[PDB]
Image (cartoon, coloured by chain):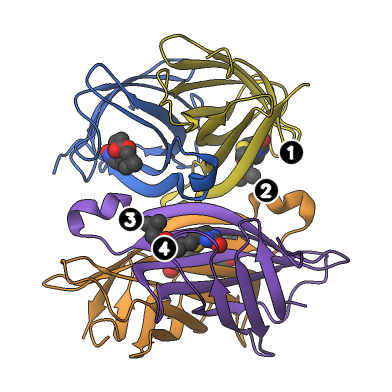
Chain colours: A orange, B purple, C yellow, D blue
C-alpha cells in the first residue's frame, strides 16, 4: 500500500502518480514523455492488497485511455506487472497499447512493450 | 454500447458500466484458472472515439483477490469495442503473477479474449 | 512431423508453406495477405520433434524477416505456438512483429497479435 | 555486426552466425528454467536495413529439446539489432508450451531480454 502509493518514473521519463487504496484500488494520473500525448491522463487499476509472504512481488495493473482536455489519441494502454518492494523498489511491467482501428487494420491494432518504474519519495 | 454483460470464448462473465467521462467499473467472473465468483474490475475507455469507423479503445484490470481466493495475480485486458448488430470487444491480455526475483522471467502470460453478448 | 509439413492458411488469408525436418527444423515460405508484404518470404523455425503423449499440442515457432525481391518492410515477425493434430488440425499462435526503429521510436517498435492456421482441405 | 556471442540480463548465452542473405544460425543456452546446455536455434534478419539510423529487425526460435532434456516448449525472440558504441539486441519473446485444449489459455509466457556483449 504505502509502498506503492507515490510518484514513479519509467525509463522513458514518463510520470506515474498513483494512490493505492487498502481495498485494492489504484487511482492517479499518468503523463507520458513520448507519443501522441501531453500533460496528465486519468488512470485506474487494481492490485493484490494481500500479497504472498514468500518474498514474491505484488501483482497489479492499470489502464490509461489516451483522452484528456488537450489531446485524444483514440487508444488505451494497460500495464500489467508487479511491485517489488525493498532496497531498490520498483514496478516491473509489460504493457499493451491498443488503438481503435477499422476491421481491415485490426491485425495491427496493438503495440506491446515493457516499462520499469522506479520511485522518488 | 459498452455498458452491459459480456461473455468471452472461455465462458467468463464481464459485467461492466461505462461512465460518461471514461471510467469502466464492474465485476469479472473467470470460468478458468485459480478463480471463483466475482472480482472487482476498473478500467478506462475513449469516451470521444473517432468517426472514421474505427473501434473504441479500452482497457481494464482485475486483481485476482476476493473473499474466496487469492491467486496473487492481476490480468489487464487491452482492446477495442466494435459496435454494430453484433457488438464485440476484441482484446489481448497480460496476466502477471507476483514472483520472487528468481522467477520474474516467467511472471507473465499473454493471451487474447473476444467478448460478445452471446452466452456459453 | 507428418502433421506439420504442409500448406496452411490463417484467418487473414495468409499462406504458410512449411516443411518439418526429422531433426526439429522448420523451413519454407510465408506469404502475407496484409501489410507491407507481397509474394513469398523465407521462413525458418523449430518445433518439438519428440512431443509429449498426454494429449498436449506440439510446441513450435518461426521467423519471417520481411525482405524479399519485391519489398523490404525492415521488420521481422515471430510466431510462437503449438500444433494441434487430428482431422481438425490447427496451429494456434501468437506473434511479435518488430520493426527496426531509431532509439526515439523504440518504445513503439513491436506489434503483438494472434493467428490461427488451418489447412486445405 | 550480429555474428558473435551475446548475453542477456539472465546470463543466457546466444551464439549466432548471421548469413549474408538473412539467415540466423547458432545455439542458445538458457541460464534459467527447464533447460540445460545448448539448444539449436534458427532465425532471420533484415540483411538490407534502413540507413536512417534505424535498428536491424530480426528474430529467432528455440525448441527446448536437446540431448539432455525436453521441456515440450518453444521460445521465439523478436527484436532489433542496434549497432554502435553501446551495441545490443533488444527483444521481446513468446514462450509457448504444448498444452491440452483445456489449458491452452495459459500456454504462452511473454517477456523481454536485452542482449549485450556483457554478461551478468
Ligand atoms: C503510437 C500511437 C499510434 C499510440 O498512441 C499514443 O501515442 C498514446 C501515448 C502512448 C504512450 C506509451 S504507453 C506505453 C509507453 N510507456 C510510456 O510511458 N509511454 C508509452
Ligand atoms: C498462474 C495463473 C494460472 C494464476 O492466476 C489465475 O489463475 C487467475 C485467473 C486468470 C484467468 C485468466 S484471465 C485471462 C483469461 N481470460 C479469462 O477470462 N480467464 C483467463
Ligand atoms: C509496421 C508494419 C505495419 C510493417 O511491417 C509489415 O507490414 C510486414 C508484414 C506484416 C504481416 C503481419 S505478420 C503477423 C500478421 N499475420 C499475417 O499473416 N500477416 C500479419
Ligand atoms: C513452462 C516453461 C517455463 C518451461 O520451458 C522452459 O523452461 C525452457 C527454458 C526457457 C528459458 C526462457 S526463454 C526466454 C527467457 N530468456 C532466457 O534466456 N531464458 C528464458
Mark 4 near ligand 2 (CB under 8 Å)?
A: yes
**Which residue carries the number 2 mark?**
A107
**Which residue carries the number 4 mark?**
B34
Chain ID of residue with mark 4: B
In the rendered image, the vertical position of residue C121 relative to residue B101, given as above or below: above
In the rendered image, the vertical position of residue D80 relative to residue A116, given as above or below: above
Q: Nearer the viewer, residue D57 or D38?
A: D38
Chain ID of residue with mark 2: A
Task: From the image, state whether disc 4 or disc 1 is nearer to you.
Answer: 4
- In the rendering, which numbered label is found on residue C12? 1
Q: Give the class, few, some or many, for how many residues have Cα within 10 Å of label 2's Cα (few <14, many ≥20).
A: some
Secondary structure under tag 1 reads: loop
Mark 2 near ligand 3 (CB under 8 Å)?
A: yes
**Which residue carries the number 3 mark?**
B107
Q: Position of residue D39 (x, y in %)?
A: 29, 22
Task: From the image, state whether disc 2 or disc 4 is nearer to you.
Answer: 4
In the rendered image, the vertical position of residue D36 relative to residue B86, given as above or below: above
Q: Position of residue D44 (x, y in %)?
A: 47, 25
Amino acid at each position: 500500500e504505502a509502498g506503492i502509493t507515490g510518484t514513479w518514473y519509467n525509463q522513458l521519463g514518463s510520470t506515474f502518480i498513483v494512490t493505492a487504496g487498502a481495498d485494492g484500488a489504484l487511482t492517479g494520473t499518468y503523463e507520458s514523455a513520448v507519443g501522441n500525448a501531453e500533460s496528465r491522463y486519468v488512470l485506474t487499476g487494481r492490485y493484490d492488497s494481500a500479497p504472498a509472504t514468500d518474498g514474491s512481488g505484488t501483482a497489479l495493473g492499470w489502464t490509461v485511455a489516451w483522452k484528456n482536455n488537450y489531446r485524444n489519441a483514440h487508444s488505451a494502454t494497460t500495464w500489467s506487472g508487479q511491485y517489488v518492494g525493498g532496497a531498490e523498489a520498483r514496478i516491473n511491467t509489460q504493457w499493451l497499447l491498443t488503438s481503435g482501428t477499422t476491421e481491415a487494420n485490426a491485425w495491427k491494432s496493438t503495440l506491446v512493450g515493457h516499462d520499469t518504474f522506479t520511485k522518488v519519495k
